[PDB]
Image (spheres, coloured by chain):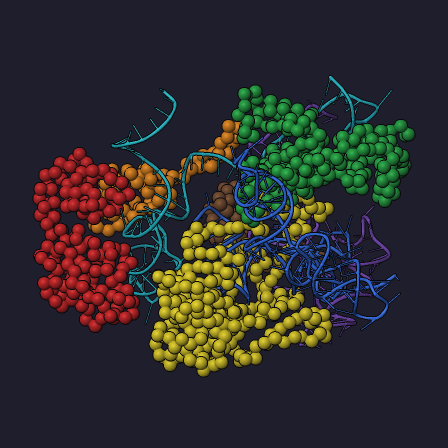
Chain colours: A red, B orange, C brown, D yellow, E green, F purple, G blue, H cyan
Amino acid sequence: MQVILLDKVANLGSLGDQVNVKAGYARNFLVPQGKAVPATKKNIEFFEARRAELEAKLAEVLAAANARAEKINALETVTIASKAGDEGKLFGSIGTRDIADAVTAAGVEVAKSEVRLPNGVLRTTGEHEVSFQVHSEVFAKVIVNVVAE
Amino acid sequence: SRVCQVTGKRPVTGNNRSHALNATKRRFLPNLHSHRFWVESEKRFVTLRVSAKGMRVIDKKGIDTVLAELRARGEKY
Amino acid sequence: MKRTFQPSVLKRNRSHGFRARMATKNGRQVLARRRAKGRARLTVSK
Amino acid sequence: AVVKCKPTSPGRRHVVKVVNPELHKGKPFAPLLEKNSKSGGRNNNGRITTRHIGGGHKQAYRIVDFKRNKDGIPAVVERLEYDPNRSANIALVLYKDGERRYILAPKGLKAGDQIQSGVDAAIKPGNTLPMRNIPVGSTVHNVEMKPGKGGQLARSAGTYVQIVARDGAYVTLRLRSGEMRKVEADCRATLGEVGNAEHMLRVLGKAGAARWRGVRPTVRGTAMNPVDHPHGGGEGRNFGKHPVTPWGVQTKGKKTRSNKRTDKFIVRRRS
Amino acid sequence: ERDGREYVLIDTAGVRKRGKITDAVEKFSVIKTLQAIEDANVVMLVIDAREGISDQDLSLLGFILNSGRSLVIVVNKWDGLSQEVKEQVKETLDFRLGFIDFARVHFISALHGSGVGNLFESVREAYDSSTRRVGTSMLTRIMTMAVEDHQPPLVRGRRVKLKYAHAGGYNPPIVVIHGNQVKDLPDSYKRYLMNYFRKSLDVMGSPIRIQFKEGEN
RNA sequence: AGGACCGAACCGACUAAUGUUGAAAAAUUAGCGGAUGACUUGUGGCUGGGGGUGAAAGGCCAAUCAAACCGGGAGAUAGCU
RNA sequence: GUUUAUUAAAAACACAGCACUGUGCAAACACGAAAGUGGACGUAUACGGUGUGACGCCUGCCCGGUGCCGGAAGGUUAAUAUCGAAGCCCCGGUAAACGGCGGCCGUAACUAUAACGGUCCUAAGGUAGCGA
RNA sequence: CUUUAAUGUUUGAUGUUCUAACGUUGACCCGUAAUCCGGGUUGCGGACAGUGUCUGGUGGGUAGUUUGACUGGGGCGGUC
């Protein structure tokens, strides 16, 4: 169908780009995910007025989502923000494994290719130490301090 | 079944046909598939069996408008 | 050699029992048919 | 093992049999036992569907599973036992768990043998593990293909498969066939095999044997009246005609493959 | 003709008949193939291994038998076929119909050529047998054996009588045997005695023909 | 021990004979085969007609079966008696 | 052994054994428009199909390597009207090829048949079964 | 115009990877001290597969019927 995006920026289409799209991408990815809202010559008018608010006020702690996204598409340097990516560097214990929650791409992951650790990892500040496996049953490690602002 | 629940479907009467123009009959199934629609207005999926003309139709009018009906068509939501 | 006539009340009745004949629309289309044709045996299993 | 019948009759002139004295003779463990069922093989609407199946003897099923579980504190082999529920021999184990269970039961057994279903494994012949911790080139039986679904390939006498490679995720094994197929990365199959590599020489021998084996005559189509089923033949038993089955086209030296979903695991076809 | 000897190209489209045009329907072409019959003493049947022996085609071979001219069987564009050939069975179904001749199967391509010599050769051999110098004597002598062995048919409690055969021409070999009446033999026994001759003196050539005349009864 | 031998029951029917408007819609009479297993049998139950089923004869499927039985189409249709 | 109940018991049908093929499980396949079900609570020493018919005894011929055979299109060998077709690779086809399964010559003692080689073909080579 | 580029393109193929439809006869939780099912979680597959339409090839398995007439019996033959 067609939508006006709600998305700040998206790899094609950005920042209240009203465009038509594939039906199979649009209804099951651009919506329902908040990255678009349907377009109609009714909707566009509503939306045009709305987006001076919505694609600004919502879209301002969302800068994080585009950045952190790389880190979870690879799962080499598994990095998400729990509160961060919009507050400076990714810091505190907060982030991935301290609640054992990190977003996956499709449940096929390299972020639980072994489990072994006694209280997880992360415990520095102003940077955040992830464990970056070197095997699948030994945890000799190569820990990094990546951020994804 | 084999019905859209919207557009209104069921297989409907046919025949093989030949330039011979022989006599036999066969019906004809529409293109329906049960597709997992996202209600959003209770933010769940209420997977309905739907046509593929209809799939379009649902889209153009929007989720809770097909789902406005069903209730108004007196039938399983 | 045996004969076509074999015995049993039991088997006879649960070849067609009244209720079983009251319990499938088609052989009940019949039940009614005959009934309207006015035969006071019906089942033939009284 | 092998024992040859001494002829005192024809009807005992070609009965080749194999005795099973290394199992107890008498009842087995009923609280792990369950009924059989017979229906002449016949369909949901009972029909002759796949001919010849049915009869036999009576036999009995035995409540079983090969998912190698209650892993905990190991078991030991108590006895082996015949059952007509496989062309093999099955066996009771007693756990230290205080569990009691039967296992499919490999060749190497001699009772009191140590069993552990523990994933660390003592790499003991006949013992199971998921293939992602196997040795290279290992011989394994009880090939599944979804992880922990429970073996369904290779659970017969002397059936095994050689592991060919385990590379990345997924393990390719050679099915007894000369078939290379990749099952999943975790997936089980039990080290080695169960033997009974001699019941190959066991025979029916006669119709009486086949009767207690439920083989109801594979009735020769080919010399029937072609009217109700066709293939070849006639009243004159004549040849020089176009040979096809009722589907109108040959079934003998024709491929088949109605599983466009398992090509993807198949690397080199069966024979 | 090349090498004096005549070759024909025939049927209607797919043949790679894309010519000056002359067969508005499916019919005219057939008028040509019947010309192809007239002119032969040898016909070659191209069949494919991947569209050959079609219904029309098997009829086409049946027709060939009428055509009364030598059959040599060619399979062309056969270097691209699959390593387990489909095709032994395809040869077997035609074999059983069955065409006593000499076959000789050819597996060529017009886009490679393999069979090229073997085709040239096969036709000559087939022509010699077909065109064979014949002669009342040979025919009578082999015939006696046959009738003694398996019995001339009897009709209405009266036994028949054969008593010589001669050759009515040789090129497609025809014989006319003077015995008992036309209906006193079934076509089958005619053929039996014919098949016998086809057997006892080589005929890698064409089907041979037998006739019966009456005068004695 | 055994598709073991002989042979009653019980089932099956090879010869003959008889009946053939019977005594009997296939028996009787008289010999005869198998008989602990490819056995036999009861009771009940289930496979349904362009269909089963079928140790296969184009058998058998309610005395009927190279197409059940029954109802309707249907006062069929029949250049034929 | 089984069988044409109500003409026909057999040489028919069956049958072990054997042979061949197809099928990797959500199996092939089979029924059932499908759902489902059977196949199978099984699992390629099986399962399904098909086919042959105990048993014993009559020898059942692998194309890949490399070679061979016919053929052309090429390669390779030629003149150097270059193109290079004939013989050979190759393409197809080829194991009565090396190598296990014939003769003929010498040789396991009436020479002759011959395990080895030669000779027909880059055939093992009457060993099996069976002898005037 | 034939022809040919350079450039603008327009579009379809293959190649690869993904996940989000879709599949999941994996495993578990749950209605429900239910091998059915449903929902949810997770594992695995994956834009496939399969199916709907349309559409080419095949198809005696299934289906309706077609296969003259003359005739010193017919069929045979020969003939119209």
The residue shown at (48%, 53%) is C19
Work out whether E211 lies above or below A54: above
Quarter of the image with the N terminus of chain A is top left
Residue A49's x, y, as percent?
10, 39
Residue D96's x, y, as percent?
37, 81
Quadrant of res F69: top right
Q: As drawn, which residue projects farthest toward the bottom? A: D112
Front-most of G131 and H27? G131
The residue shown at (87%, 29%) is E214
Front-most of C9 and D222? D222
Quadrant of res G62: bottom right
Quarter of the image with the C terminus of chain A is bottom left
The residue shown at (53%, 79%) is D23
Front-most of B14 and A116? A116
Horizontally, residue D133 falls left or right of residue A30, namely right
Horizontally, residue A20 falls left or right of residue G125, namely left
Work out whether H40 lies above or below E213: below
Residue E27's x, y, as percent?
60, 23
Instruction: Report whether residue E190 is seen.
Output: yes
The residue shown at (68%, 43%) is E96
Residue G18's x, y, as percent?
65, 62
Q: How many dots with numbers? A: 0
Work out whether B16 lies above or below A88: above
Instruction: Report whether residue E182 is seen.
Output: no
